[PDB]
Length: 48
Length: 49
Image (cartoon, rainbow over the protein chains, first blue to last red):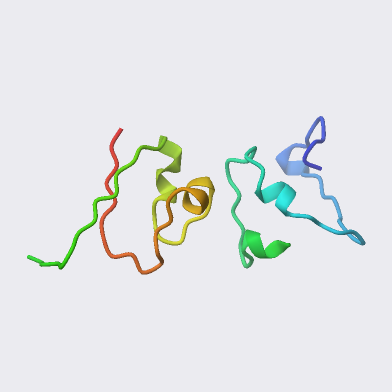
């Protein structure tokens, strides 16, 4: 999803379903590649 | 109009976009690893280019 070569337009935004896997969110929230990382109803650290 | 027992002037330099991280209850590189304000901070934050 994040490393996809080309992205969709906002009006026809793509949706990917995630299921049956282990999500290591550190890989995301510890990366310095994102300008905005805003989490609602959850705290990023707790995601793990 | 106010008195206080002590004042602490904590001085440092950051880049513009990180100024928002110098505030109570913020997250990010600065707020996490460099300088963290308490949730009950009582004071002023001054920044200029």
